[PDB]
Image (tube, rainbow, N blue to C red):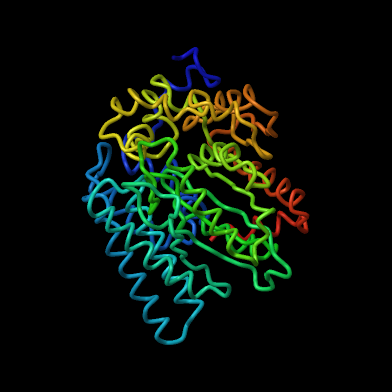
Amino acid sequence: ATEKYYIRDAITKPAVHHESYQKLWETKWKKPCEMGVYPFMFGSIKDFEPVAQEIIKKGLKEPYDWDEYAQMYFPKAEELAKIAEEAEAAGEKEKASEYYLRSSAVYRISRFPTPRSEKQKYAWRKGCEVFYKGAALMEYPIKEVRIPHKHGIEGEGDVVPVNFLLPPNASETSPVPCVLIITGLDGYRTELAVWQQGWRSKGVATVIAEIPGTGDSPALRQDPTSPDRQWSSVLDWIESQKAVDSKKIVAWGFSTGGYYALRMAHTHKDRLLATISLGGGAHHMFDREWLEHANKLEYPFDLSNTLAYKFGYPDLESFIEESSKFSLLNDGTLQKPCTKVLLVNGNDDEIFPIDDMFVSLENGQPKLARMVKGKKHMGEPESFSIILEWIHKLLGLDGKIKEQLAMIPS
C-alpha cells in the first residue's frame, strides 16, 4: 500500500487534526474561517471562534457524538438568525442577507462532514431555510428550483432541488451560458452558492445540484446509474429555460463532484459543452488500500466512513466489498466518447489519489489536464485561476478572472 500510489508512504502518516477538535481548529480550520473561505463561505470568525472555544473546553474529539457536536453550534446559529429577522423587519436588506447567510454557515459546520444524526439532519433543514432567506435578499437573488425528477425510478425522490441564478439581461433573444456546479461530500448547494454572483457578473447563469446521497439529492445511493437519471432531469429543466443557451452548459464538479462531472462528460456528452473535475476521482478512490488509509489523512473528519454513508452502506467494510462497481473504469464509462474534459488536482491529494487523473488519461479520448505539483486536495489556489481562464476562453467571456475570484472570500 505504501508503494501503490503516487504519494507513496504519505498514506501512513496520520494528520494531527484527527487528535482533537482543538487540533482541527488550530492547525486546519481557524485560518480559512478568518479568511472567510471553504468551508466557512458567508461565515465570520466573530461567529465561529466563540463556538470553537466552547467545543475545545468540552475536549470533543474522534469518535464524535454528532448530536453532542452539532448542538454546540445551535445557540450561535439561532442568535444570527434572530439578528437577520430584526434587520429584515427594519428594512435593513443588506444586513438581513449577511446575518441569514452567517446563520447558514454555522448550521452548515454543525452537520459537517455529512448529516449522520437527527440534530445534523435538523441542521441541514434549518441551514437551507436561513440560506434561502439570505439568498432572497441578495441584490441579484439566488432562488431554489425544485426540478421535477421526471427521469426518477422507484425509490427515488420526486424533485432535484437546485440553486438558480440568471443574469439580468438574459432572454430567449439573447441567451447566456450556464455553469452547472456539482457539489461535494460535505459542501452542498448552500456552500458552492458562493460562486454564483461571480458568474452572474460575467453574464453566466448558474445551477447548483448535489451528488447522490448528499443534501436533497433524490438519487438511489447504491445505484451507480442514479446520477445519470438526475442529470437527465436537470438538463431537461435547463433546456426548458430559454434565457439559457443549452449549447453552452459547462459542468464544474468540486471534490467528489469531480467524479460526477467526469462521468456525465460521457453519459451526457451531446448535452454538455464541457465538464471540469477539480480534485475528483474515478477508480482508485474505491480501492480497499486507499479507503483503509484516507480516514486519518488531510480530510478534516473520517473521509472513507463518510464516503461509505454517502453510497448508502452501513459501515466501511460493506462499502469496500462493493465499491469497485462505482469505478468509471470497471463500469465501462471511460471507454465511451466524452465532451471536452478538463482535469485539475494537486499531485499530493490524500482525499482522492492523483493516480485517478492517470486512469482518466489512460482510457478513451484525450482530456485536458493541469497537475499542481507540491499541493494536496484541489491544488489551490492556482487550480481556480487555471479553470476560470479555460472557461472564459471556452465561452468567450471578458477573461477578467482576478475580478471574479476576488468576489469569493466572505
Residue 223, picture quadrant:
top left
User: Vertically, is 14 above or below 132?
Assistant: above
User: Vertically, is 30 above or below 224?
Assistant: below
Residue 204, picture quadrant:
bottom right
Q: Residue furthest bottom?
A: 90
Q: Find residue 387 and report its horizontal and vertical position in percent.
A: 67, 45
Front residue of 333/188: it is 333
Q: Find residue 88 and report its horizontal and vertical position in percent.
A: 42, 81
Front residue of 98/147: it is 147
Q: Find residue 278 and report its horizontal and vertical position in percent.
A: 58, 40
Front residue of 179/107: it is 179
User: Vertically, is 264 above or below 35?
Assistant: above
Residue 75, picture quadrant:
bottom left
Q: Which image quarter is the N terminus in?
A: top left
Q: Going by the image, does 394 lie left or right of 275?
A: right
Q: Residue furthest top?
A: 3
Q: Find residue 337 and report its horizontal and vertical position in percent.
A: 64, 32
Q: Residue at x 63, y 48 (%)?
A: 271
Q: Going by the image, does 221 lie left or right of 238?
A: left
User: Vertically, is 86 above or below 124?
Assistant: below
Front residue of 40/26: it is 40
Q: Residue at x 50, y 43 (%)?
A: 257
How many marks overall?
0
Q: Residue at x 60, y 58 (%)?
A: 239
